[PDB]
Amino acid sequence: HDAWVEPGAAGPRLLLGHPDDSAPVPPEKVRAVYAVDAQGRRLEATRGAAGGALPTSVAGQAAMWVLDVDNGYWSKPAGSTTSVNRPRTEVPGATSGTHSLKFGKTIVAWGPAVTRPQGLRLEIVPLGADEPRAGATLPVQVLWDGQPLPGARLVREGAPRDTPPVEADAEGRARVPVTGGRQMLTVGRRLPLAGDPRADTVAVSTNLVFTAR
Ligand code: NI
């Protein structure tokens, strides 16, 4: 599951799931959501209490949306295959468990502001400041804990499943092929976690969603 800001015909919305199969992010899972304007200024945003929508005034002037989601704890008993969203300390038969974090960035107006790192624990930062055409490559920097992540594996969600990931270079930089229309890039990491009874792994996913000219 990814958590992302989908740029729809009705305005941006917060989704959790997969591009063709998604549901709104539950409010209790949103740690932060905000926009950045074309001059780099942070714009606050919350979904409306009746209709669940992000504010039009912010959406219309956003350069990029940023989403930070705590997807909580996951585990499953020995002998099962599907994880449930409960910590291993409450699931008899579980011995491992994950704390799952999800981040998303959606670019809606290209310019210098979108190249500024936002401080997401795992982040894809565009190195291009121009709206990409299909067929171009978009250079990106992958960051982890605020520093380049050499060898990060970037997945093109629109490409066939069987496509090898784009591997970031020694500087954590990659030249990602741009496809037509709306597209999503993802990077994930799963790492050991010490000091949490409820999980021995921390899983982090991040994405960059954008639309080609
Ligand atoms: Ni999933």
Image (spheres, rainbow, N blue to C red):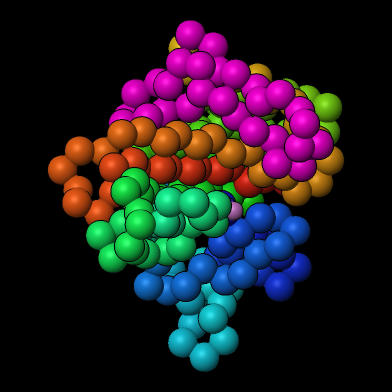
Nearest to the observer: residue 174 or residue 17: 17
Farthest residue, direction top: 170
Residue 157 part of the magenta-drawn span: yes
Q: Residue at x 75, y 68 (%)?
A: 9
Farthest residue, direction left: 195
Residue 76 lies, in percent from the top left, at 43, 56
Residue 205 lies, in percent from the top left, at 48, 43
- Image-based side of 47 in relation to 176, left or right: left
Q: Which residues are magenta?
A: 142-170
Residue 25 part of the magenta-drawn span: no
- Look at the picture and state if 49 lies above or below 100: below
Q: How many marks?
A: 0
Q: Quadrant of the N terminus?
A: bottom right
Q: Residue at x 52, y 91 (%)?
A: 50
- Image-based side of 45 in relation to 52, left or right: left
Q: Residue at x 29, y 42 (%)?
A: 200
Q: Chief secondary structure of the magenta span?
A: loop
